[PDB]
Image (cartoon, rainbow over all chains, first blue to last red):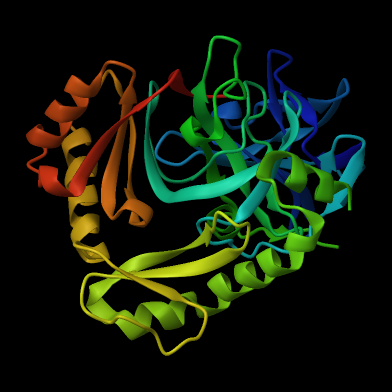
Length: 198
Length: 154
């Protein structure tokens, strides 16, 4: 299938999450996503077909993971933006206060700014440190999803946030949103991955 | 392109404001280390900020005198605590929690407000207060703030 950031994928035919970014580890193809989305070996499927399995993951503590796919998968250096697509051109980390947008199967393509870095989150499953905070809204299912700058610089993958009863924080003012994401670079660097850029 | 609309929609960044914004974003990235070295141990962080007229600017903070920088276009701000200072407080909270904390959402160093922010669920400020105190962190460098909803993985 066409591996693109922001699209929905299921795990063990039981839960939903979003694709982060297409990557390669040598000759191996794959994609980064959130660690809480699945456990090692868990099976990932896009549109019904098995595309690969979770090769590794850390959560809590961190919230990262990557899925190694089959040779038949097509890796595109893009991020879904509604019907359009933003081109991934690199992984340069943006500064606090920078404009950043995210994509996920639940809320689509939303923008906001980076408001804090190295955030420690008190998740029911355990604390996760080193997260970056932004005020673009998101909802459940958006996890693993891509966070990218207006110029295509890949920032990270969606981890969590202060969702409301409706399942997201789009209903509360930006000034009060806490949307967190795991930084991309430490993921690429830990699993010796290389981002697919265009 | 199609991204331009989202920028105007959620950030009020209009087309004529894009270039200035972009220029400011490049400066924050390329100068960051330089700004950090220049202020040494008195460095209190940097970040991009928006004026009320629309323009953007790069702000650098310091706990010492400074008054200005060797790099043009960098509004300097004098603040009480230094980054190393706030970082130590951050470490004290990370440890205190490393030992759960119902009502406490998250915490982080926030240079923008020269303080360590501790977010708690609405009407859970007490748990925040206790968290800080039990960690033996200088309550002077810690700001507790309410946060709606519940923090959770999504």
